[PDB]
Image 1 (cartoon, rainbow over the protein chains, first blue to last red):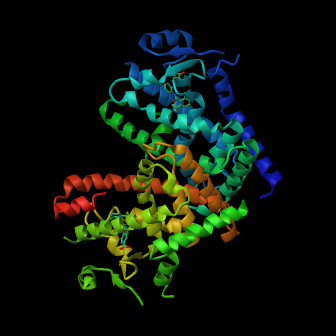
Image 2 (cartoon, rainbow over the protein chains, first blue to last red; image 1 turned 90 degrees about the horizontal axis):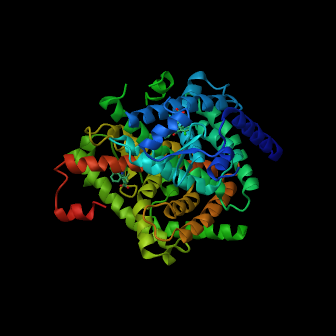
Image 3 (cartoon, each protein chain N blue to C red; image 1 turned 180 degrees about the horizontal axis):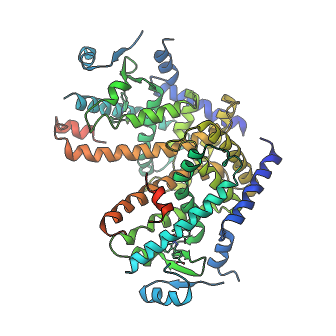
Length: 257
Length: 251
Ligand SMILES: O=C(O)c1ccc(-c2nn(C(=O)c3c(Cl)cccc3C(F)(F)F)c3ccccc23)cc1
Ligand SMILES: O=C(O)c1ccc(-c2nn(C(=O)c3c(Cl)cccc3C(F)(F)F)c3ccccc23)cc1
């Protein structure tokens, strides 16, 4: 509720974000824009085969990539969970609620941060050692030629706000501490925390992007688009489960819906 | 420009009063007993009130909704700058906007136990609405759940007038030809809305943020309604009547 308290809250979260997420947006942009480090580019199947001898990927093609993308998701859930521990008040909440906040929250956060790794033309993979193009992913077979595209569409819009990491660290906390999750036992203390985080985000954006009229409101409006991407991904995953499939214990739990 | 924001705000509340016959203030007075409405809680109650059922109620809610679209279209005329936008862009904004607004404004007629109907001359219970045939009676409850959360923000008409304008001027609707002027207008509205909530609810921390957060839930509920409406079109044949009427009320 005090300006210096809010700046303090912001530094705390930026700190834990740096410590919890190995690839920041600043590091990714440096790789993406050529600033002094350059990735191997995957645009076709021969490039894909060429990639393994260069990067440590692959841990039928469209399947190896989907499963590889899912294995990457398990890491993302782990990093997000670590970051969330350090949000003031989160570990004090009721255990069930802590679990529920993570249940719905991780996917919206993965896609928020996946935007840090993308441009119009493709996405960084394997901790920035590779770069897979959108048209290659778009051209994958069966239902897999479509799981990545709506992420690209969001990112292009999302990256237009030019947020930096110190902006994102607070935004991510706001996503987790949302009292509208299905099944929360005690909404009042969850919401109380978000008043603090929203207050910090409001000031952080005013200071960091003072020329950006209504960035705060515009950034919150983006939570609408995040929700829509998660709906589609959960549905496309119930289709794979019945066709081939054959899901990490972490992924098994987040997929109860 | 604080005076500009208070000026913009009083303008819309003025126009909103003139465009929408049943305000939230007026509806809340009727809900609380502060002329009592006819209450529909069962099937015999329905037959007596006017002077297959689940379809008659759905069709009745749509005919009512189409009346509100004309009222919303008129209110949008009064948003400063809106009539100067490209006509194509105006149609597109209303096309995608009306649903979110109809749901926003439906919450003013709603409480835990039911909803005002026919300009406040009736009251339909939620316990009646919850229990309808499998396809129907399931498009309703998510509205009630939304409203209760929404009505907990305790907004009044002068808040909603600006909130409604904000929905209308969303520069992300598919097919917009010229987004800059739409967004420039929406900046003014958000500034005006922000000021409105601080003055009106000086004790309500971060209400502005909380209200914008609700637009996430509005989009999700409209999506679901758009989905259930693709199901009735292919499954329910009795929803035919005059071909002209299907033409009038399809939207
Ligand atoms: O080193 C590896 O084995 C490997 C390492 C990474 C990938 C891979 N990750 N990914 C992502 O989308 C991703 C990223 Cl890049 C970072 C964090 C979270 C994600 C998440 F959304 F999947 F959860 C992809 C998309 C498309 C194609 C390949 C990949 C694949 C393989
Ligand atoms: O003012 C009125 O007479 C009135 C006005 C609205 C309702 C009402 N409509 N509704 C719908 O789901 C609905 C339907 Cl079913 C068809 C088309 C459009 C809608 C819409 F309003 F949501 F947009 C509801 C659900 C739950 C509770 C009350 C209602 C009822 C009465």
